Every structure is written in structure tokens, then in C-alpha cells.
Image (cartoon, rainbow over all chains, first blue to last red; front, side, top):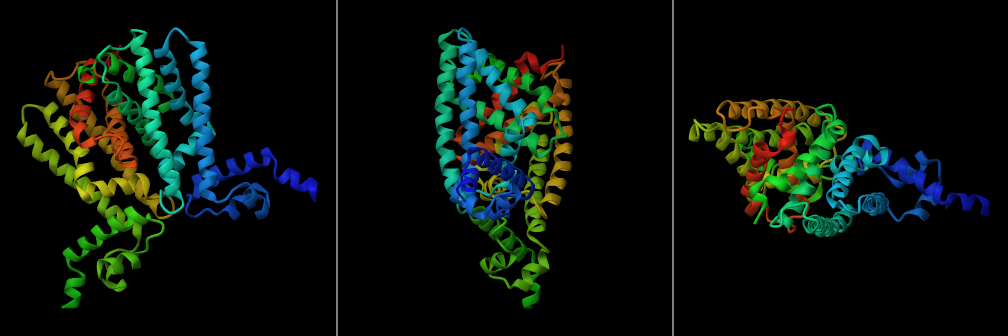
Length: 211
Length: 210
């Protein structure tokens, strides 16, 4: 009784539920997938999954937010790696995001679901509203990064940083979305470094990016 | 007769416009053809005459919008017959601005990005659209090469890499704006963004062959 409860409630069980959910959501869509289905696929009881999670929206939010937190961790890492070169920090973070969309199961499936396997309606509206706020936060953080680069003299002093930040997110999200939609249409893993290099060349060179 | 009107183009189009409004609010998965009939003021018999299923209905509106873009390309080519780079610029600016300003485009894109799971019957729509996307990349490459021919873009521009980037740049702006429409003014900034895209073709060394 209590031994079995402890195992049901464990972090490793939780992780497995989340990974199995990603797989089921990517195959059949969020709308058609129930918590009970996820539990059966994860080899846990219905009681266990409903202890772990209030609903499938909250489950999905958790994955999405853990991914966002992994990105933050890598930034802290790359900063300590290239403390004299913020533009390389930014380059490597962006190339890692793009390549991981192809190569890492968790990121690939999460992004596939965000873009192609989840309607932002019903209980998912609360997930969209939260991620909307995180988008805005992201733009401010991206502006900050660009300003770090300007202060290091590595980007134009008159860069339009908000325009630049909007373009960062759209350029990178578009590449991810288009590739996931049609993964044989181009080789995102191979071309990722070129594409990020082109983005950073844009900031350095395109006159409509300057005041 | 009742029948003439049920089968009439105008009724079909009211059904399609009402489906867009419903799908955009409720999602494709929750929305039945019966619901769309009721909202359009037609019988269930009438809507199932026009459409066998939601995907066929959605596919039709998707393609009607794609057709209107094709039409704009033809019109811009006649406005700028000696200037393919301006044709391109104006088509792209139009697409971006119309995402904000035109109801049909705004709702269609919102559904494509945020309100339709590509599963079940929707996989055949994804397959059709994947083929259209492959065609689009080749048309974009051709347009770029014609610009190169006119000496308006660099002789060594990497056209395929450039094409991939065009679609991603433009789709990413649309998607990001529709996700968070108060986060930036896409209508206002569209012309700057397209100009920046074309400046990238002209200037960025990694867009050119070594």
C-alpha cells in the first residue's frame, strides 16, 4: 500500500508520465488524448495521474515551462563560458535551440505539439495566456542581450533593439515551425548554424535595423 | 427554390465565413458541421451537401486564400514589369499587412497556427499543403533568380537557402503576431520587416556562395 504509493508519487514516475504524454500528444493531438489514456500508456493508475496533475493543460504547461527553464540554465552556462563575447553566447544559444528541435526528443515533440498538435481553446486558453506573458518577457530579455552586445561594441550602437528582438523570435520560431511541418523539405540541423549567423549578420549590416 | 438557394455559391461562402469564425473561437476539433450549419442558418442537410467533412471545408478556404495571393502576384507583375524585386517586396508586405487587416486572412492564419490539430482527416490537408509548400519554394527560387538576372540581387545569392528563409521569416512574423497581437504592431512594421529581409539578401555574406 504505502510502498506502492511512494513509487506512484515519485519524480521518476512523474517524468515518465510527462514523456509518454508528449509522445501521445504528438501522435494523436491534445484534444483526443485523455489523462486516463496517458496513465494507461505510462503504466500507472488513473489515481496516480490525477494525483500528479489537475488536468492535461497543466500537464502540458509543465513540460513547456520545464523546457523554457532548461534554456535559461544553458544561457547561464554559456555566459560563464564566453564572458568576454556576448554575441557568441547569443549565437550558441540560438544554434542549440534550432539543432535541438531536430535532435532532442523532448524539444522536438514539445515544439511539434505547440505548433501542430494543440488547439489553444478550452483549458488550453490558460496555457496560451501564460505563454503570451512569457513571450513579452522573452522580448525584454532578448533586448537586454542585444544591449549587452552593443555595450561590448559588438553590434551597432544605433540598433533598433525591439525591432531586432521581434525579428529574433519570429526568425527562429518560423524555422522551427516550418521544419516540423515538413521535415524533409530542408535540413534544419545542418543549416542551423548558417541561419543563426545570417540573423546576426542582419543585425550588423541591414540599415533598416538602425535608427 | 429552397434547393437553389441551399446549393448557391453565396450560401457556400456564408458557410465558409461562418466556419472560419467558429473554428477561430472554438477550434476545429470541437466544431461540428452541424454547429456550422446552425450558425450559418442552413439545415444540416444543406451543409453536408456542400462539404463531407470539416477538413474538406477548411481545405477549401485555405486554398481560396492561396488563390487570392496568386492573383496579387499577377497584378503586381503587371504594375512592375521591369522590377521583380518590387513585385516581391509588395507581395510580402501585402501578406503581412493583410494578416492583421483582412478578416478572412487573419482568421485563416489564426486557425492554421493555433486552432487546428494536424491529425485524423487533417493529415490529408497537411499533405496537400506540404506539396504546395514545395512548389512555393521553387517559385520563390525562380523569383530570386529573376532578380539576380535583373542585377537586383547578388550574383552569388544562395537561392534555396534564401527561399527557406523567406517562408520562415514571413510565417514566423504572422504566427508570433497572431499568438500575441498586442506584443508588436505587425501592420505598421510590415514594410520595415520586408525591407530588412531584402537587405539581408543584398548584404549578408552567409547568404552567398563561397
